[PDB]
Image: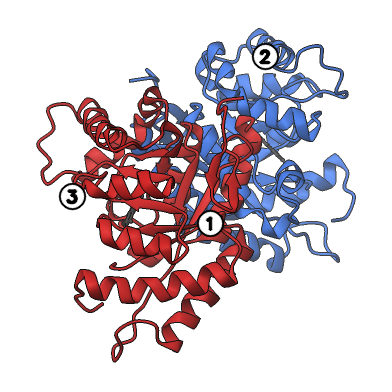
Chain colours: A red, B blue
């Protein structure tokens, strides 16, 4: 009905109309005495991806940087072994959480299916050329180095559009474009609540929307509850986001949010 | 802004615009060897009402019947001691969950502030005369002895309206009228999801709306999860309901739903 195509992720396909797709956030704790690839840290990633697969995750999101400061070179050595292990061992598409072109390239060559850019191709535009060449889905998230909005939503849609132009000029197909309001980036707590309240506006751009609100500090600001007490707050934002038409949510609490998403879907008629 | 009055509950007042008001469901386990008023069962009610007061409840809902079969006379002897204890010991308005006129009368004379009728004044119309005389708020819930809908929402609004006419003919003031779509009553699981999806229609009638979905079996039907596993499902329905404009939610999990309601409120701008 609403999407006339599926997200093609190489060996896996995501239907955009069936259900809200849960992206599970891989927790990625490095080893303190290693250069990446070590058995403790790879095995904890795989076990965690398996747990999230079993809890209802549709996508595993994997990042090079969320303890120790790393170079691009060191970010590659962490993330590449984990992508190879998770993709061998867990049958779910993987997104590689990076804004760097070379990191994105290796992550796909190592098995990643979707690029997840927090800089919307703006930090490193060549990443869109990476997405264009491998023919992968790429998430362009709203971000900026300031909070000088004239009008938050208007500006956010303008900024997303500048990202889409970079992606398309680089030969990215419309079907590989997912957008994200980048909640928690370049935004006051009041702007975050404003974006949530007005999220349906993003639908005019014609692309699927991913929302990432999980455990973020605007929830803490409303509830006055620390990061480990943010499950109900996150739930509310997942529910509002599915009701405003988002196709994906990016969450830590996969069991719980799958359940809320499934109920939300049944009620709104998706 | 949306309500130009507050709910007057005798000594307590509820602002309809500030926040979603949480009604907490008193669990009411009778003593098996007693005629009501016993210390084990009164003390467990008070302790539970105190716990819910502390978790964010705005209203305590108290029912005469939810183990052993009771007469009207026996329903009065259970509920009246608990209302006296809870109202002495917990500073929150109490709603008396009954459809019977005489039960409602004693419950108010014993300290209850709001009448909560699952039969919308239809089982015992004289209850509206009770509400009219004591000048209490009365909740008229959608119910019927069949599921022969021509058109669910149209019919539900027609039926609510027949309840409002009984309440008003009896001298109930518009400001003491709260409505409820009676989710889980006279409705298939698919009709329940249909009512949830179309809940905002109830707003045309001009009264505040209370939603009661907590742990109900339509959640179980969607999620295939038993009553103790319905917290995330309930959460979704509370979130959708606040987003569709409900003023009250009636819940068992008061801590959790207060948190979701508070986050929902911050996002929608209530
Ligand atoms: C890659 N990230 C990181 C992030 C922040 C924390 C660290 C709080 O999870 N948020 C997001 C993200 N990626 C996308 N696409 N959307 C997010 O909201
Ligand atoms: C008084 N009740 C009982 C009830 C069912 C269970 C037993 C599942 O909680 N639901 C409701 C109720 N009262 C109101 N106003 N609204 C309800 O949804």
Measuring 62% from the left and 48% from the top, which residue is drawn there? B233
Labels in figure, total: 3
Marks 2 and 1 sit apart, C-alpha to C-alpha, by: 46 Å
Marks 2 and 3 sit apart, C-alpha to C-alpha, by: 54 Å
Pick whichever of labels 1 and 3 is earlier in the sequence: 1
Residues under numbered marks 2 and 1 in contact, where contact means CB atoms less than 8 Å apart: no
Q: Between label 2 and label 3, give the one nearer the viewer.
A: 3
Nearer the observer, A146 or B140: A146
The residue indicated by pointer 1 is: A93
Nearer the observer, B19 or A219: A219
Q: Residue furthest front?
A: A133
The chain under label 1 reads: A
Q: Position of residue A162 (x, y in %)?
A: 22, 32
Mark 3 CB lies closer than 8 A to ligand 1:
no
Residue B125, image quadrant: top right
Q: Residues within 10 Å of mark 1 (few under 14, many from 20)?
A: many
Mark 1 CB lies closer than 8 A to ligand 1:
no
- Mark 3 lies on a secondary structure that is loop
The residue indicated by pointer 2 is: B157
């Amino acid at each position: 009905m609403k999407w006339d195509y599926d997200l093609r992720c190489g060996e896996y396909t995501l239907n955009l109309n069936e259900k809200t797709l849960i992206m599970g956030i891989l927790n990625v704790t490095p080893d303190s005495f290693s250069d990446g690839g070590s058995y403790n840290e790879v095995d904890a990633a795989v076990r965690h991806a398996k747990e999230m697969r079993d809890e209802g995750a549709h996508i595993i999101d994997i990042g090079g940087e969320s303890f120790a400061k790393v170079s691009v070179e060191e970010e590659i050595k962490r993330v590449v072994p984990m992508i190879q292990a998770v993709s061998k061992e867990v049958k779910l598409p993987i997104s590689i959480d990076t804004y760097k072109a070379e990191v994105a390239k290796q992550a796909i060559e190592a098995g990643a299916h979707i690029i997840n850019d927090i800089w919307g191709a703006k930090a490193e535009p060549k990443i869109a050329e990476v997405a264009a060449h491998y023919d992968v889905p790429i998430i362009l998230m709203h971000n900026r180095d300031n909070m000088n909005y004239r009008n938050l939503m208007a500006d956010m849609i303008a900024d997303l559009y500048d990202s889409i132009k970079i992606a398309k000029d680089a030969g990215v197909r419309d079907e590989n474009i997912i957008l994200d309001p980048g909640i928690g980036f370049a935004k006051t707590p009041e702007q975050n609540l404003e974006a949530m309240r007005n999220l349906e506006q993003l639908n005019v751009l014609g692309y699927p929307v991913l929302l990432g609100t999980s455990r973020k500090s605007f929830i803490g600001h409303v509830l006055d509850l620390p990061v480990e007490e943010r499950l109900e707050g996150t739930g509310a934002t997942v529910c509002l986001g599915i009701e405003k038409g988002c196709e994906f949510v990016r969450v830590h609490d996969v069991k719980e949010m799958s359940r809320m998403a499934k109920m939300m879907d049944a009620m709104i008629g998706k």
